[PDB]
Length: 202
Length: 206
Image (cartoon, rainbow over all chains, first blue to last red; front, side, top):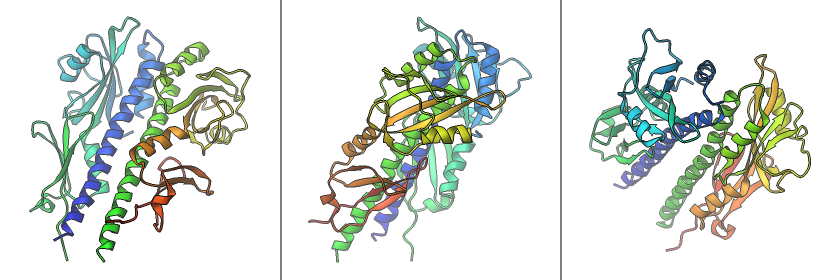
C-alpha cells in the first residue's frame, strides 16, 4: 500500500532524467547553432557554410542541417535535393522571422526527408540586426524515442503536445494500467511528458 | 523502526539532489564543449586574431560560469584572451595542453589554480585541426570552480555535498559537515570528468 508511493517517486526519478536528457539535447543544439552564427565570416559564404554544416552533421540526432536565405530557400543542405526547397510557409520560419529569435518547432513530417522531426531554427543577423539568413537543425522524433527507450525499456512513458497530439510513447501501455502518471512539461517546447509508475508487486 | 522509514526518505532525497546537481554540471560542461567545438569548425583560415578576440569576448559576455576564454597558437602562446594579460602567457606545460596535442581531441582537465587569474578552475580545451589533421591552434574555456560550488550551495544550503577527484583531492564542498553526521553519502561520477559527487543524507529528527 506504500510500495505505491515508492514506485511513484521512482517514476519521478525517470521523469527528470528523461526531461533533462531532452532539454540538454535541445540546449546543446541551440548552442551549436548560436556559436556557428557568431564564428562565421560575414557575409556568409555559401560554400563554406555547406562545408560547416557537413562537418557538424557527420550525430544521428539530425535528420539534417540546413541554411536558408532571407526568402526561405534552402541554400546549403546536408541532404542532397532533387528540387529547390522553400521553408517560408513553415511555422517556425515565420515565427523566427518576426521575433528575430531562435525558435523550437513542434513535431512534423519533414518536407525534405519525409520522417517525423522537430526543428531548431536560429536566425542570422547583420550589424543593424536585420535577419539575413537562417540556420536550421532538424532532429528525428525517432531519436528521442529511442533515447528514452534505452534507459527505460520496460516502463511506459508518453509525450504529448499542448493540444494532446501524441509526439511519441516509449514502452508498453499495458504497464500504465490502473496507474496515474507523474508528468511535466519540457523547458523549450510545449511537450508534456507523462511517466507511468510500475505496479506494486510481490 | 519508523526511524528507518524517515531515513530511507532522507536517503532518497540525497539521490534526487545527486542527480539534480550532476545534471547541472554535466549540462554546463557539455554545452561548453559544444560551443568550443562549433567555434573550431566555423573559423576561416588563416585565423584572423582580432576576429577571434571578438568572438571570445562575445562568447564570454554575461556568462559568470567562465573564468575566461582563450585562444592558443600551436606552441601554446595565448594569442587571444578575455582576460587582460600583463605578460606573455604560454600553456604548453599544462596537462590539458599536452593531452590535447597528443590526442587531437577535446580535453577536460582536472581542477587547478589558474596561472592567469589565480583562482581555482578547470578547463575545456579543443584542438583546431588542419586539412591534414595537424593541430594548428587551441580553444580554451576556463570555468570557475566556485561558480559550480555556489550553484549547488544556493539550491541546497542545508545538505553537505563533496566533490572529489580520483586521487582524493577535494574539488569543492558545499554545506556544513555537521549535517552529515552518522551518514553514508549517496555518490556518483560526473560524465565528462572523473569527479565523484558525494551527497550526504540529512539525519532524522521528528
